[PDB]
Structures are given as C-alpha cells and as structure tokens.
Image 1 (spheres, one colour):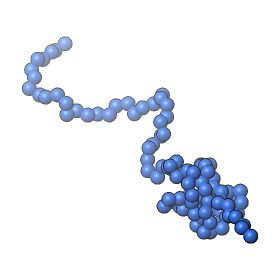
Image 2: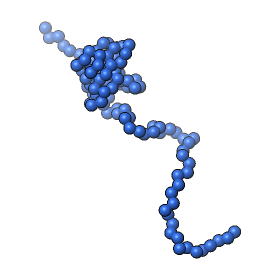
Image 3: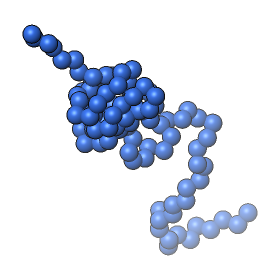
Image 4: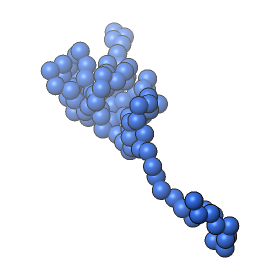
Length: 101
C-alpha cells in the first residue's frame, strides 16, 4: 500500500546490468582480439623458420608469424600453402617446383 501520483521526476537515467547469461548456447566465448582469421586459409605463405614433423616452424601469412606444421622438412625462404588449421598451429605444405631439364 501507499501510492503516490506525484510526478516531477523524469524516467530513464537508470542502468544496471542484471543476469550475466547462462544455460544458453556458447557463442564464440569472449570475442576478443588476435582471433584467427580464416580469410588467409587457402593462400600462400612464406617459411621464416625451418619446419619439421617433430616441431612446427614459423611462417609469415599476410603479415603475421604463425606456427606451421608439415609432413616434410621445409627450409627458410620457401613458399607454402596453408591448407587447414590444426588448432594453434597451421597445416601447410610446400609449393612444388618443376625440373625442366
């Protein structure tokens, strides 16, 4: 009980974030920075660090240095194609030469 029709105050100007959000489908989960861009998948990259099957190397895709793995041993200065992403590493294979001799 009570009730007051005295209105001299204005509405709005009140913000307060209730309910974080749970029991729903996880969308992305923290859309933060440095998120892997799939737009560079299927393009050429260059080998900056020697790549081995035991330890991934470093390739420069666009302008970013990524860890890259391969089934063969890749030396520096080579050109590779990024086929897929295995996680925090990229799946790359080396461009093929041609012996016209």
